[PDB]
Image (cartoon, rainbow, N blue to C red):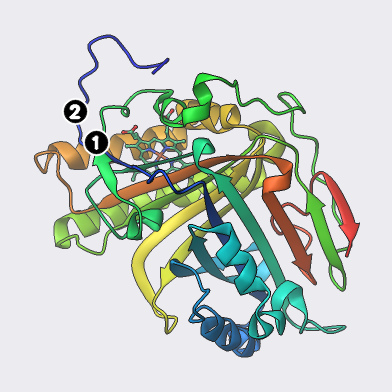
């Protein structure tokens, strides 16, 4: 590990995914229905829900709700496979093909469709968990193990196997170009990303907190998490953050549960590192979590985790049908009409 300090002894425990040898990829698919009122999205969401129960459906799927720009909401499925061939057979299923790639989105539709499908090579992937929790993304179906490789700047990079042999820099260098405003409503658009973009899903789960911890999380952490995500959304070029969403997770039936996450894409892992290590909003929430840890013998019922991947252009498929121009990758890079 390159960045680990001498005689490193972390204050808090943490766990990390330990992938079996036969696993080569994780498919992480984000599929969204975009609307101004959730009633408009009900029909699509019903169809997609049933598709996930196919024999080729994902090993795990979360539902979440995103409040986007200017009154648009995204109803999102976060779906995981451990076998790309199974994912491809799922997409090919006639029931999935009824709605895949926004097929039902007609002209002048009140809803949009988008999908961001990432096929993650395992050597370009790492996870971290504040507890031995088997309901955190891939930990629903991958074992996890205790690790010392955390609680220092650069630990995320060190946990990703390929960082020992690659700097993981963008071919575009250090500056994300100014966003542009696409005429994206009424169109079917595919965006091509540059190599070595970095995707993070970083999650907060207060479902097991008693009153004390819950009041602290809601009163003292979440407001600054909201501030952090807003800053990332509004300052793409300064930060290198292509896209950031704060989403609240839901039951199968759509009810909001006590879980959230930020899903963000960055021009490179280095951009994500520099924001995390430097910005005051992450400074503030990091400090509060360690304040909670000390007050609870370094075992809070609040659970945090993240999944971080570094992606090649060919690893990610980005499709936006009748979407608001601020959605996802639409402001950046190369676009084509499908
Ligand atoms: C916009 C939302 C967030 C982003 C993008 C983000 C990003 C990151 C990244 C990339 C790291 C790894 C740093 C490294 O290893 O170099 C990290 C570490 C950490 N973050 Fe966050 N984070 C976010 C929200 C939060 C929240 C809400 C909390 C607490 C409630 C939090 C607490 C921590 C802690 C405690 C660590 C240290 C983990 C360890 O290595 O043991 N973060 N964060």
From the viewer's perspective, is 72 left or right of 199?
A: right
Q: How many marks?
A: 2
Residue 177 location, quadrant: top right
Quadrant where the image shows the C terminus: bottom right
Question: Residue 257 at what x, y percent from top left?
Answer: 35, 71
Quadrant of the rendered image containing residue 248: bottom left
Give SS at disc 1: helix
Where does residue 166 sit, x and y in percent of width and height? 59, 21
The residue singled out by tag 1 in the image is: 290
61 in relation to 251, above or below: above
Q: Quadrant of ligand 1?
A: top left
Q: Is mark 1 within 8 Å of ligand 1?
A: yes
Q: Which residue is mark 2?
A: 11
235 vs 294, left or right, is: right
**Element on which disc 2 rests:** loop
Q: Nearer the viewer, residue 246 or 334?
A: 334
Which residue sits at x=59%, y=87%?
A: 47
Q: Is residue 5 above or below residue 132?
A: above
Q: Label 1 vs label 2: CA separation?
A: 9 Å
Give the farthest residue toward the top: 6
Question: Mark 1 packing: few (<14 Cα in 10 Å), some, or many (20+)?
Answer: some
Give the percent coordinates (x, y) of residue 118: 62, 53
Left or right, residue 172 beside residue 140: right
Chain-order first, disc 1 or disc 2:
2
The residue lying toward the viewer, choosing from 315 and 37, is 315
């Amino acid at each position: 590990m390159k960045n680990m300090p001498e005689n490193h002894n972390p204050q808090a425990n943490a766990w990390t995914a330990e992938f079996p040898p036969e696993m080569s990829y994780v498919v992480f698919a984000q599929i969204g229905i975009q609307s101004k009122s959730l009633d408009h999205a009900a029909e699509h969401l019903g169809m997609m829900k049933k598709s996930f129960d196919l024999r080729t459906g994902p090993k795990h799927v979360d539902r979440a709700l995103h409040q986007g720009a200017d009154g648009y909401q995204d109803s999102i499925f976060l779906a995981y496979w451990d076998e790309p061939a199974t994912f491809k057979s799922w997409v090919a299923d006639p029931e999935v093909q009824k709605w895949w790639s926004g097929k039902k989105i007609d002209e002048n539709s009140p809803i949009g469709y988008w999908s961001e499908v990432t096929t993650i090579p395992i050597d370009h992937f790492e996870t971290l968990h504040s507890g031995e929790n088997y309901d955190n993304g891939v930990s629903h179906f991958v074992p996890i193990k205790h690790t010392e490789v955390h609680e220092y700047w650069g630990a995320m990079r060190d946990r990703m196997p390929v960082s020992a042999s690659s700097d993981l820099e963008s071919p575009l260098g250090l500056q994300l170009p100014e966003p542009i405003v696409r005429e994206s409503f009424g169109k079917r658009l595919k965006v091509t990303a540059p190599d070595n973009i970095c995707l993070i899903r970083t999650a907060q789960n207060w479902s097991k907190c008693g009153s004390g911890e819950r009041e602290t999380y809601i009163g003292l952490v979440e407001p600054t998490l909201i501030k952090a995500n807003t800053f990332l959304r509004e300052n793409a070029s300064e930060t290198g953050c292509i896209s950031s969403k704060l989403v609240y997770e839901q039951t199968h039936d759509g009810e909001i549960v006590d879980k959230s996450c930020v899903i963000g894409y960055y021009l490179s892992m280095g951009h994500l590192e520099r924001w995390t290590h430097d910005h005051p909003t992450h400074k503030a929430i990091y400090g509060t979590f360690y304040e909670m840890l000390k007050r609870h013998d370094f075992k809070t019922e609040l659970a945090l985790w993240h999944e971080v991947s570094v992606l090649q252009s060919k690893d990610i498929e980005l499709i936006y049908v009748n979407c608001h121009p601020s959605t996802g990758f639409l402001p950046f890079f190369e676009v084509t009409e499908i």
